[PDB]
Amino acid sequence: ARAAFLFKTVGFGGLQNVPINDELSSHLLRAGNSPWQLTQFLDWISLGRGLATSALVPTAGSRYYQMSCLLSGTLQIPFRPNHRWGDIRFLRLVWSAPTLDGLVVAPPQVLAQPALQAQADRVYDCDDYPFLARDPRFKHRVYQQLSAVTLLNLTGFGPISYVRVDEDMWSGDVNQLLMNYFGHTFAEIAYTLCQASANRPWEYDGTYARMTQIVLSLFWLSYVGVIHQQNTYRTFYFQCNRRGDAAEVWILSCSLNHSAQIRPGNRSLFVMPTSPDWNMDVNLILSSTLTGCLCSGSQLPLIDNNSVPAVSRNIHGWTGRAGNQLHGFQVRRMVTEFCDRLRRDGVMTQAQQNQVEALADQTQQFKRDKLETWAREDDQYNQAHPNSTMFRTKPFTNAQWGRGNTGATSAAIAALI
Amino acid sequence: GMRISALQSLSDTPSPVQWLPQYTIDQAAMDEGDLMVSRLTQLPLRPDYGNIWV
Amino acid sequence: FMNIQLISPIDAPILRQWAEIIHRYWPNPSQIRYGAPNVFGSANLFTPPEVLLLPIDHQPANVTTPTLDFTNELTNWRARVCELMKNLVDNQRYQPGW
Amino acid sequence: ANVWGVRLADSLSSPTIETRTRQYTLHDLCSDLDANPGREPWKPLRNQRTNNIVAVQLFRPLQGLVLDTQLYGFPGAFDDWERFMREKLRVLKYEVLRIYPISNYSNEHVNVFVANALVGAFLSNQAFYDLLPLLIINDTMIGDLLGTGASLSQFFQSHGDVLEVAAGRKYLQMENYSNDDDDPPLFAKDLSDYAKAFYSDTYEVLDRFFWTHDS
């Protein structure tokens, strides 16, 4: 179980403010004035069947980052030491209730008065605000989404996911529930688990918690290439027909060909992508979201201070003195890792590998060009309108395009088995 | 801003006690002093008289 | 009715006793659990979900073949009521016509 | 110095030394049931004006009276009540010693909940034979009651990993309590069911229980 409820806000990208403005905020709240957007997010990415795109939200990672920016900017009003909610405005917006249900447009007298000036990289505690401390169910319901936001905002790279292997997790009820998900895609399972988590918070060792941990382990082990049709994990695995494409689909399948031998004991790690490609990959974002929704009911091992930037260190329940390190990979090289592991196992030929690599190279070319063009447009806009100063996507640098530690994380995930 | 010291105390005594005052160099107007006394005065009342001669 | 010093024990002892009986022997409220929020959710506005409130205390049964028992709160109330009736019936001021 | 209407003395003093714990064994249960000397497990309370006794305070084995008073058949006086308690406890002591031989079970601990419930049920004439096997702790004081699904709802029940117990009476009101200005205040602990207790091993499970439960 978890005893501390700390979270971290977004940091400025060299700008003078939070990188969100009025236009983007009105775009987010066009169909619902709740800052807790995690359900509406799920309706926009459309189960991951295609490349979602908007004029103001070019990608899925763009919307995820903009939700983070809005929460980080707006939650600083009720968390001031005086703990007042309806007295001032943040970018024409005010809070509806002491219980933070939604946002409305400020009344004229507050519009006349100036706005709150937020700060970068703040760390807050949920127990400080009295209305959160009073109601535990409300605190957990919002802390799920705050945990997801912290997981995005902890470092400069993409979202962080958690992988665990343990034999004693399995039980009768877990088997009974897992059989129902045969033939479903990863996105559908993620949707249903997120809705179930929203309705009722999970026990420490409930059926749903162990279920979602097993699902994450299956997805990541299939993603690396350790587990396939001919080498299963108690007959269960994930299958992709079109590896390397812009919008991959993974399907949960059952097979009786083989069962891989599993060493006893409990093992786990934290993994994350570093290349900007994660902005267009929905499975990784959903994996991080599932970890966030899990984090409310359970307590995860601490992350080492040496794998995180300076400002994000020594957070009470998140980072620690000698915790686990972060395993970072970038997408294009992992496809080569997948193909190599399959070819060594003997289930794949050289020509098939050639075709997969060619398709993945085309995909990476397209993605890199689009992201660079959008970055250029944002720079131009920031120069033209100094009173707006916004960002549509999380910033990145060129050095993030190269590979790094990919082989190490691949080896570690294969060594989890 | 406190000091560590138990609540020592005294007991009930059914008698009035003698008292003698000490003064200080602080100065005040006499008309003001009489204004407060008349405000705090418990009079009028009827006292016992006693004896002139014994 | 709020404080019992305003009633004379020598002038209206019956009402004094009745007020004491009401104040200390009225039934106690209780709550029970119900529903399955993992599918149906809940529509409880002011009370927490999964909880149903009652004005009368509830105790579960230990036996599936019950036999008469008077330890229940409702009988205890009726006992107070009947004793208080007896007090004013035994009155010699009531009796003369009887 | 001033806190609304109450005044403070502007100096501090707190205790600095704390005693130790002492388990509850079968020998001490028997000794409390004896009540032969002025070691009786209850003390009297007197009026400040008329100097007559108006109530009693209850101790280790006697803290279990949760049913209404009439079911216990107490007398209105003090001396008669003392006699009645001595007699009933004397009978119960031999009923206990019948089950547990003294030379065998002398060096073992007692389950306090069961002692209080057994005393109360014996006084009220309920079936007390069910509690007797629980009178010696075997694994853990809380765990034994948790693992026993076959118990009586009159005293305690189980909600998963939380043990719900009925808080017993602390004060017992004699015949003379007229709600006088010198009658001692009983602080609502002389009622039938003035509280409810929830026992567990970790406060996290307790508060996650009161999540669902109304407060």
Image: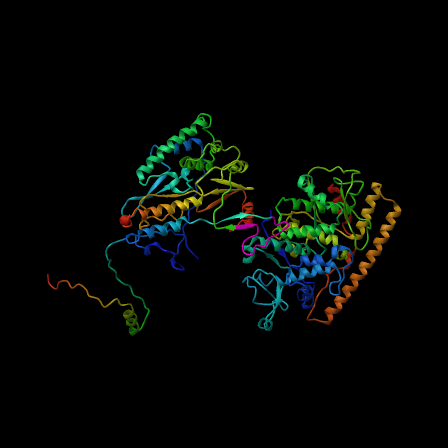
Q: Position of residue A86 (x, y in %)?
A: 56, 66
Considering every residue shown, the one lying at the far right of the view is: A351
Task: Give the magenta range.
Answer: C36-52
Q: Residue A346 or D78: which is nearer the viewer?
A: D78
* C39 is within the stretch colored magenta: yes
- Whether residue A245 appears in this view of the structure is yes
- Residue situated in front as seen by the camera: B2 or A174: A174
In the rendered image, the vertical position of residue D76 relative to residue A331, given as above or below: above
Give left or right: position of A294 versus D6.
Answer: right
Determine whether, in the image, residue D181 is placed left or right of residue A285: left
- Please, is residue D61 above or below residue A24 in the view? above
Q: Residue at x 32, y 47 (%)?
A: C87
Quadrant of the drawing holding the N terminus of chain D: bottom left
Q: Locate residue D114, reporting x and y percent.
A: 46, 36
Is A299 left or right of D111, judged from the image as shown? right
The image shows residue D190 at horizontal and vertical percentages of 39, 45
Quarter of the figure with residue A282 = bottom right
A244 over A380 or under it: above or below:
above
Magenta part, dominant SS? loop
Between D121 and A410, the one nearer to me in the picture: D121
Residue most extreme to the left: B54
Q: How is the image coloured?
A: rainbow
In the image as oriented, which residue stretches furthest toward the front? C97
List x then y, in percent, for residue D44.
Answer: 33, 41
